[PDB]
Amino acid sequence: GSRTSRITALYERLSRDDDLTGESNSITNQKKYLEDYARRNGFENIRHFTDDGFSGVNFNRPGFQSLIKEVEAGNVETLIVKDMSRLGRNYLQVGFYTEVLFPQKNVRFLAINNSIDSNN
């Protein structure tokens, strides 16, 4: 109608070619990671956008499409990611998402393994 409960976006991606071997060598593991964050941070409706055989061009993915689907509908009030590498190092397009795209719902993007948009 007018006012309702939107959501939080938790999008993750694990790679089988990494030399990690331990936690991130599956799927639900890194998922739970972001979870530990969103909870330690205080985010609601933490939606988990799973990864499986993701391309290496930029955006537009299965689980990602769900993530973006929430963004377009104006639900994803926050974005929790292991790092900006998921969406790409191309801060031009990635930024567009967080600066012009996400504004619809007032987003707080998080990149654990890289400075999302801070200073220090």
Image (tube, helix red, strand yellow):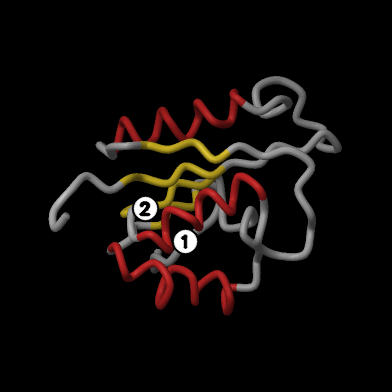
Q: Nearer the viewer, residue 2 or 12?
A: 2
Q: Are marks 1 and 2 in contact (CB under 8 Å)?
A: no
Q: How many marks?
A: 2
Q: Nearer the N terminus, badge 1 or badge 2? A: 2
Q: Which residue is mark 2?
A: 76
Residue at 27% across / 48% down in the picture? Answer: 6
Q: Where residue 103 sits: x, y (%)? A: 33, 70
Q: Where residue 113 sits: x, y (%)? A: 56, 48
Q: Amino acid at mark 2?
A: Val
Q: Nearer the viewer, residue 113 or 32?
A: 32
Residue at 32% across / 45% down in the picture? Answer: 7
Whether residue 7 is situated above or below residue 71 in the rendered picture: above
**Quadrant of the rendered image containing residue 35:** top left
Q: Amino acid at mark 1?
A: Ile
Marks 1 and 2, how far apart at CA: 17 Å
Q: Residues within 10 Å of mark 2 (few under 14, many from 20)?
A: many
Q: Nearer the viewer, residue 45 or 19?
A: 45
Q: Which residue is mark 1?
A: 116
Which residue is outermost to the left? 3
Which residue is outermost to the front? 1
Q: Where residue 68 sits: x, y (%)? A: 50, 57
Residue at 31% across / 54% down in the picture? Answer: 77
Residue at 59% across / 24% down in the picture? Answer: 28
Whether residue 42 is situated above or below residue 90 in the rendered picture: above
- Left or right: residue 115 versus residue 2 is right
- Which quadrant does the C terminus fall into? bottom left
Q: Nearer the viewer, residue 95 or 73?
A: 73
